[PDB]
Length: 37
Ligand SMILES: [Cd+2]
Ligand SMILES: [Cd+2]
Ligand SMILES: [Cd+2]
Ligand SMILES: [Cd+2]
Image (cartoon, rainbow, N blue to C red; front, side):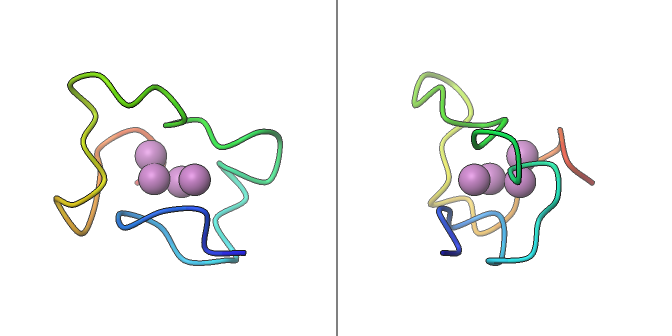
């Protein structure tokens, strides 16, 4: 699943376990993040 607001369901960055799973300062609402990019 997209598992994110900053990533789609294809983010292979999240294909391991959602690299941004940390809902701390890596807010997904952002619509996009800066770890997978
Ligand atoms: Cd994300
Ligand atoms: Cd991601
Ligand atoms: Cd994710
Ligand atoms: Cd990310």
